[PDB]
Amino acid sequence: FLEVLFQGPNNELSPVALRQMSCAAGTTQTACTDDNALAYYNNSKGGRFVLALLSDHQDLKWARFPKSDGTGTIYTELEPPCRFVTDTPKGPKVKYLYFIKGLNNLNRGMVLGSLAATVRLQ
Amino acid sequence: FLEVLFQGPNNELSPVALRQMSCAAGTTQTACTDDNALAYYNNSKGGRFVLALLSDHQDLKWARFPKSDGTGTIYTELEPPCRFVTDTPKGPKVKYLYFIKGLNNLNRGMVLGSLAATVRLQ
Image 1: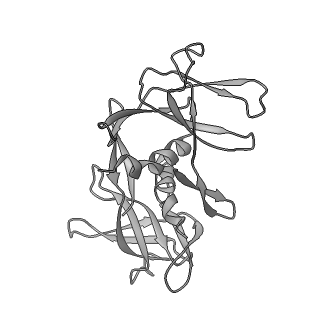
Image 2 (image 1 turned 90 degrees about the horizontal axis):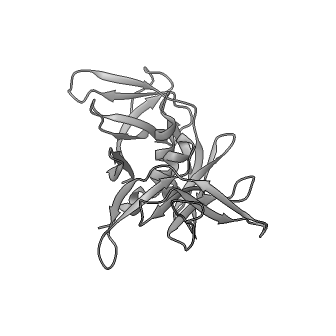
């Protein structure tokens, strides 16, 4: 379970869990059927603020998240993939890291430095 | 020893050690006498690219690094401090995190997410 420390003004930084849940990505909103990736997020003013998708496919383009109210669903658009490989039982794998479109430059960093040591485990 | 994964184009990300060395910070370039903080860096095109300073003082403002040639010295300017506290033998401490002035918004993030789990160890 990844983390990232959050800055509570007056310049006070404090460790905040980098959450993960499974989701149904695809090339099309429509092609979003079964779950194929993992979503990394934080709950922001508006509950649930996903940042990146970790997946075994590099084919993805959109992600599907049913609203945290049971109201409807939210379809977020993905950026191009980021390939890297980590040791996995049954063989090492190339996981693709998808940064949600428009993902902040700091947030962008935040994750990259947050799971950096995770990818390095051999 | 902290880390951060580095992106080698064609979108390939790869774990890269987030290095640390001690340094002599102070309020003045001049006041930079004995070592009082730890510097986090990466070797970039121009060897040695420090990003942040971890220190027990919140008084710092400048840092001193003798050139990686034995030529001279480089005085980098620090940004305002970032207080947080972590468990330490002999009592928990408030360490101050100083981001070098002009530190990129991604690099900014990179470190924050890189030592996030480090600060959370109780």
